[PDB]
């Protein structure tokens, strides 16, 4: 019993973190096979970041200007290329700790673990979600760029995020491992404001199922609703519209608990309209939206 | 910027988890040097757990009855002993991945990371605190016993917790790595009720400092207080008494922010008396007490 914000075990990713230095900039890289992946802004001065021309800045860089250190051992850079907003540094040594891996581009509402790193050294691991406005709410200090987000399926690491940017509002932006930003963000120190950070409805519903499984039941009510009726209320409260696809995804939790998805929507509707009245659900005073239905099933079933 | 509930990177501990089976019971063990540590209740049937005589049950067990598996490889058990509520299984192979380590017994209010495991396989990592009633609020399913709690200081793992028990109220009890339960709990399926789960005041104050550092400032008010005045209010709200030792520990965060500890106590006093009025602090609608002052300094400074 109990339900925690849980990250994947980080060891497989710890084995891939390296330090990348270009001139006076140090950040983190991800070493998979004989390629180190890092943010292309490693080549920028903070001055450069105001209006960088990355192709032009990169012309002034050679393989020997990219200093890659794995623990206390230097890696030899034998090639470099820019793919979107990441650099791929080809090294002469395959990472002996390379796990089975995939690069995946996640959808808003999907969760992942972040291994926050500084100077190629892991500092901590925490759980994030891709927000509906394609930001994440992370914990990243100067030096954390190139820290990665991932999911694990048994022994395969799916890398989904690399940290690039903090917005003036203190939320975070980054790329997939092909170097494409999530959302509209750019690797430039400019006016970038995030859109509405809506609540991930299907994740709240999943977490309410987790609450019922773990004995927190006070919020269950005598009501039901329809998707359209629920969505009128979701819209008013800046919740994401619930789709039949979301209802289908919640089916296993519905089955496990015997609470119909639309009954749980009616419980959520009352919580939105009535508030928590000073009560908590799984130790939270707000409706938690950074557990996916898959997360809830995984944690409630004990997948390794 | 940003402030997350962050666990230590788990890799060093992942390298120590093994499966222990005795008859029909499978749980987790911790393999350090040539010793595997596990809960002594591995030797119990669920029937046994109602009133176990561990010395008597252990007489019926031989080295060859303790099946220890590290990944898909069997370890040879060459001795076994009971120390308090843990078994120490001596194996013929030192764990080649043994990190630098210590066994520490933590105080209530101290935080640690848990690597939840099933069948010796890591499932997830999350951050816990030793509650003032010597329970923890974990996420543990059947098979999770022997999962461990730890802190890391650079490259040294301090193991502080091993999971043994779930109370009928769904909170968790366990031991240090000498096999001594935290608090009054026993490894028996009996009436064990937890005492008051008071709020860890010094940790709330630390987290309010973290909030100010990360730009959440709305709760700062024009007031101050005294330890005695604050403590009258703490007592009323089931907060732990704040001591001068706690004030001394918050000194570095006081210095960093320029907010005197007693001024922050007066902000906390108003939050207790007035509530949050539907506002949040670092994404929480309640006052978070599972960050120590050391955690806040570590996460705000980026220690690896």
Image (cartoon, coloured by chain):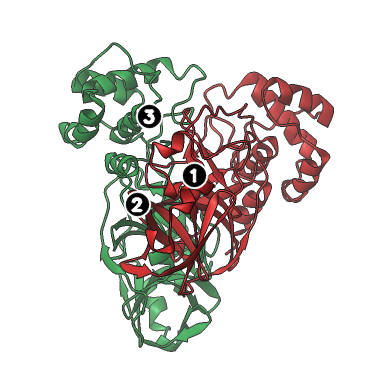
Chain colours: A green, B red
The answer to whether B85 is drawn above or below residue A257 in the figure is below
Rounded to the nearest angstrom, the CA distance separating label 1 from label 2 is: 18 Å
- Callouts 3 and 1 in the same chain: no
- Callouts 1 and 2 in the same chain: yes
Whether residue A52 appears in this view of the structure is no
- Callouts 3 and 2 in the same chain: no
Whether residue B188 appears in this view of the structure is yes
The chain ID associated with circle 3 is A
Query: Residue A60's spot in the image, x, y percent?
Result: 42, 83
N-terminal of the two: label 1 or label 2? 2
Mark 3, mark 1: which one is toward the viewer? Answer: 1
Rounded to the nearest angstrom, the CA distance separating label 3 from label 1 is: 23 Å
Query: Residue A215's spot in the image, x, y percent?
Result: 39, 26
Rounded to the nearest angstrom, the CA distance separating label 3 from label 2 is: 34 Å
- Disc 2 crowd rating (10 Å Cα; few below 14, some 14-19, many 20+) is some
- C-beta proximity under 8 Å, tags 1 and 2: no
Identify the element where label 2 is drawn: loop
The answer to whether A16 is drawn above or below residue A213 in the figure is below
Please give the residue where the numbered disc 2 appears in the rendered image.
Answer: B23
Disc sitting over residue A211 in the figure: 3
Q: Residue at x 56, y 21 (%)?
A: B277
The chain ID associated with circle 1 is B
- Disc 1 crowd rating (10 Å Cα; few below 14, some 14-19, many 20+) is many
Query: In front here: B38 or A254?
Result: B38
> With A188 as the anchor, is B157 left or right in this view?
right
The answer to whether B171 is drawn above or below residue B237 in the figure is below
The chain ID associated with circle 2 is B
């Amino acid at each position: 019993s109990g339900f925690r914000k849980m990250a994947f075990p980080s060891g497989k990713v710890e084995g891939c973190m390296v330090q990348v230095t270009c001139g006076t900039t140090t950040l983190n890289g991800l070493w998979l096979d004989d390629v180190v992946y890092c943010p292309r802004h490693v080549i920028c001065t903070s001055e450069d970041m105001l209006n960088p021309n990355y192709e032009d800045l990169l012309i002034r860089k050679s393989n020997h200007n990219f200093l890659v250190q794995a623990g206390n051992v230097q890696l030899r850079v034998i090639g470099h290329s820019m793919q979107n907003c990441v650099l791929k540094l080809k090294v002469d040594t395959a990472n002996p700790k390379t796990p089975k891996y995939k690069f995946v581009r996640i959808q808003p509402g999907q969760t992942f673990s972040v291994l926050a790193c500084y100077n190629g050294s892991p500092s901590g691991v925490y759980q994030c979600a891709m927000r509906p406005n394609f930001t994440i709410k992370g914990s990243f200090l100067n030096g954390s760029c190139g820290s990665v987000g991932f999911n694990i399926d048994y022994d395969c690491v799916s890398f989904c995020y690399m940290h690039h940017m903090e917005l003036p509002t203190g939320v975070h932006a980054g790329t997939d491992l092909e170097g494409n930003f999530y959302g509209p963000f750019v690797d430039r120190q400019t006016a970038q404001a995030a859109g509405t950070d809506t609540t991930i409805t299907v994740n709240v519903l999943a977490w309410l199922y987790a609450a019922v499984i773990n004995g927190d039941r006070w919020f269950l009510n005598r009501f039901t609703t329809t998707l359209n009726d629920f969505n009128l209320v979701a819209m008013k409260y800046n919740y994401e519209p619930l789709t039949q696809d979301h209802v289908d995804i919640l089916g296993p939790l519905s089955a496990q608990t015997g609470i119909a998805v639309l009954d749980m929507c009616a419980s959520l509707k009352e919580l939105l309209q009535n508030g928590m009245n000073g009560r908590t659900i799984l130790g939270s005073a707000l409706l938690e939206d950074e557990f996916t239905p898959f997360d809830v099933v995984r944690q409630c079933s004990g997948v390794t």
